[PDB]
Length: 253
Length: 248
Ligand SMILES: Cc1c(C)n(Cc2ccc(-c3ccccc3C(=O)O)cc2)c2ccc(C(=O)N[C@@H](C)c3ccc([N+](=O)[O-])cc3)cc12
Ligand SMILES: Cc1c(C)n(Cc2ccc(-c3ccccc3C(=O)O)cc2)c2ccc(C(=O)N[C@@H](C)c3ccc([N+](=O)[O-])cc3)cc12
Ligand SMILES: *c1ccc([N+](=O)[O-])cc1C(=O)Nc1ccncc1
Ligand SMILES: *c1ccc([N+](=O)[O-])cc1C(=O)Nc1ccncc1
Image (cartoon, rainbow over all chains, first blue to last red; front, side, top):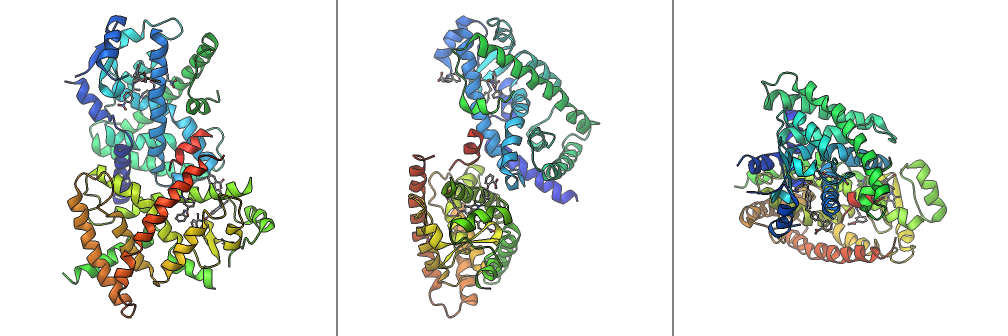
C-alpha cells in the first residue's frame, strides 16, 4: 500500500542525510551562487594556500582519499537499508564491493556541472579544462564522468530521490559472486516499488522518469569498466604510486 | 495525566514486539522448558551444521554480526518513541551512538540464565562453562556480562517493563555532544514517569523497584566503559570491507 512505501521512502531519506555530508541540495547551493576556482598550476599553487588539502599525482592521490572516505560513508548508508544487515555476510561484502563505484559517480554528479567539479568539501572548484589537460596518463580520469554527469543531472533528481536510487544500486543481485540472490532481489523489488512511487510524486510532470532513471545504470556500468582499465595502466607507468588498501579490495578486475 | 502514561506504556510495547524479533517472554520458554547445546569442542563443530552460520575467534566475531543486526532493530525501535523523530537529526544519532551498547547488554540478559546463553535466534545454548573455557582474552570477555545478567533478571522484569526502560536509556541527556538537550530530557522525564507507573501496576509487591532499576545503569555504563577497553586489546590480536561494516 501507499503508506508502507512512503514510510520506507522517508526511512531512507533520513539515513542518506545522516550518512552523507555534501548532499546534492547543498552542492547546488554552492554552484548557483563561495569557492576558490582552480584552472592552471598558478592558481592551484595559490590553492594550497587558500583551501584545506608532481601536479597530476598528488591531485590523484587526493581524489582517492576522497573516495576512501566515500566508501566509508556508503557502507554506513547501506547498513541502514532495511534487510541488508540480515544477509549472508559474503554477499554484504560483495554487494558493497561492486556497488560502491556505481554510487560514487552517481553522487559525484551532484558536485559537477557543464564547467567543473567541487573539490575538498566545497571549498574549491576544479574547472573541467584543468582536468582535460593533465599529464598524458592522468588527464582523462574524470572526462567521461563529466559527460555522464550532464546526461544524469538532466533528470533533475534531488536527494529524497537519489537516496532510494543509491539503495536500488547496492541491492543488485545481478552481481557476480552472490550466494543467495532471492532475498537480495526480494528487497530490491521493494525499493524499486518504493522508488517508482517517489518519482511519480516528487516529479509528477516527468513522464517515464522511473524508466529513464533505471536506464542510467547502463551508462553507469560502462563508466566503471572504463575506470578499472584506466587504473591498470597507472600501476604500470607509476609502479611507485601506492594505492589505498580499502580501494584495493574493491579491485578484483 | 494518569491515563496517558498507560497509553504510552502500550504504544512502546507494541513497538517493542514489532521491532524486536526475539522477546524475553519468548526466549524464556527456550531456557526453562528444544535447542542445541554447546558444552565443549566437539559439540561446537557439530553446531555449524545444524544451526547454519581459529575457533574462539569465529565465535566472538559472530557475536558482532548480531550486534549490527541489533543496532538496526533498536534504530527502527527508537523512531516510535513519541517525538524522538522530531529531535534535531544530529542529536538523534548521538543518542543512538551511545545508547546501543547499554541497550544490547540489557537484552543480552534476557538470553542468559546462570548456565550460559542462547544463540542464533535461540536454536542454540552455549554453556557458560564453555564460554569460561576460552583462551585469553576470550573466556572472560562474556563472563562479566554473565554477572550483570543474573543481578539484572533478579528484578523479574517483563517485556513491557523493558519497553519503557529501553526507551529511557536512549533519551539520556547526559550523552556527550548533544545540541538541544531540553526536549530530550522532556521525553526522558516523561518516560521515567511512565516507567514508574508501569512498574507498580505490574509489580505491586516488588518494592522500590523503580529505584533499584535506575541503580542498574550504574552497572550498564560500567560494563560498557569496561567492555570497550576489551575491544581495544583485541585491536592487538588478529577483508577491509568487513572491518568497515563493523566499526565499533
Ligand atoms: C584533486 C583533489 C584534491 C587535491 N583534493 C583535496 C585533497 C585531498 C586529500 C589530500 C591528501 C591525501 C592523502 C594524504 C594527504 C593528503 C593531504 O594533502 O593532506 C590532499 C588534498 C580533493 C578533494 C576532493 C576531490 C573530489 O573529487 N571531490 C569530490 C570527490 C568530493 C568533494 C567533497 C566531498 N565532501 O564530502 O564534501 C565529497 C566528495 C578532489 C580533490
Ligand atoms: C560464536 C557465535 C557464532 C559462530 N554464531 C553464529 C554466526 C552467525 C553469523 C556469522 C557471520 C557473521 C558475519 C558474516 C557472516 C557470517 C556467517 O554466518 O557467514 C557467523 C557465526 C553466533 C550467534 C550468536 C552468538 C551469541 O552470542 N548470541 C547473540 C548474538 C544472540 C542471541 C540471541 C539472539 N536472538 O534474539 O535470537 C540474537 C543474537 C554467538 C555466535
Ligand atoms: C577520482 C579518481 C580516482 C579515483 N579512485 O582511485 O577510485 C576516484 C576519483 C573520484 O572522483 N572519487 C570521488 C568522486 C565523487 N565523490 C567523492 C569521491
Ligand atoms: C557480543 C560480542 C561483542 C559485542 N560488542 O562489540 O559490544 C556485543 C555482543 C552481544 O552480545 N550482542 C548482542 C546484542 C543484542 N542481542 C544479542 C546479541
